[PDB]
Length: 50
Length: 50
Image (cartoon, rainbow over all chains, first blue to last red; front, top):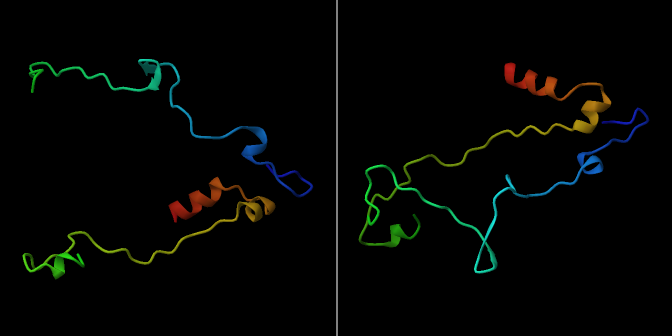
C-alpha cells in the first residue's frame, strides 16, 4: 500500500520472509543428528532385489 | 563444442536446440503505477490480453 501522503508499505513491514519448509509436520534424525530421507515402497509385482 | 572440434575422433558436432536470442524485457515501476492510481493486475491483464 501507498500512504495517501507519499511513501509506501512493503511486505517486509507486515511480515517476515524466508525459505523454510513446505511442511513442518514430519521430521527425522539418524543416530541423533539432524537428517532426512525418502522411504520407498515397491511397485506391485516388482522384485525387491532388482 | 569448442573442444570436440579440436578432437580428431569426432566431426559435424552441433547443438540440436537453438541459441539465445535478444528479447525485450519489460520493467514496470510499481511506485509510479500506484502513484498514478493504476492497479498492477490491470497492467498485466492489458499486456496479456492485447
